[PDB]
Image: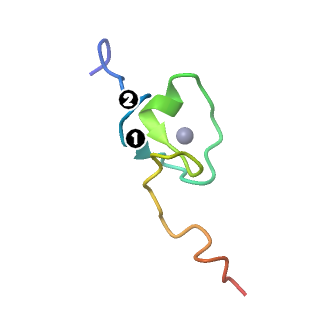
Amino acid sequence: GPLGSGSEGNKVKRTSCMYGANCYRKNPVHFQHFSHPGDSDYGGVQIVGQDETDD
Ligand SMILES: [Zn+2]
């Protein structure tokens, strides 16, 4: 529920964002609720490139 919900922006494993590598919105509090590739807590790994072998 809202009001008193959102405290994971320091030492926690954030959940990967619904876009994973294509996120488009960007807020100061969204980075704390969803993780992204390139962060020490990213953990989505939903087949985005696969060892760069798409030829
Ligand atoms: Zn995001």
Q: Which residue is mark 2?
A: 8
Image-based side of 44 in relation to 27, left or right: left
Residue 54 lies, in percent from the top left, at 68, 82
- Estimate how packed mark 1 is, as few (under 14), some (14 to 19) or many (20 or more) residues with alpha carbons within 10 Å: many
Q: Position of residue 25 (x, y in %)?
A: 63, 34
Q: Residue 14, labelled with which disc?
A: 1
Q: Alpha carbon of mark 1 to alpha carbon of mark 2: how far?
A: 7 Å
Sequence-earlier tag: 1 or 2: 2
- Compared to residue 35, the image places residue 4 above or below, namely above
26 vs 10, nearest the viewer: 10
Quadrant containing the N terminus is top left
**Is disc 1 placed on a helix, strand or loop?**
loop
- Quarter-of-image position of residue 53: bottom right
Residue plotted at (67% across, 77% down): 52
- The residue sitting at the right extreme is 55
Instruction: Say which amino acid is labelled 1.
Output: Arg
Residue at the extreme top? 3
20 to the left or right of 10: right
Q: Where's ligand 1: which quadrant? A: top right
Instruction: Give how far across and how far down residue 45 sits, in percent.
Output: 47, 62
Q: Is mark 2 within 8 Å of ligand 1?
A: no
Q: Which residue is at 46% across, 30% downward?
A: 32
- Mark 2: few/some/many CA within 10 Å (<14, 14-19, 20+): some
| Image coordinates for residue 46, horizontal then vertical, percent | 48, 64
Q: Residue at x 52, y 32 (%)?
A: 31
Image position of 10 with respect to 41: above or below: above
CB-based contact (under 8 Å), mark 1 and mark 2: yes
Task: Name the outermost residue toward the bottom.
Answer: 55
- Going by the numbered disc 2, the residue's amino acid type is Glu
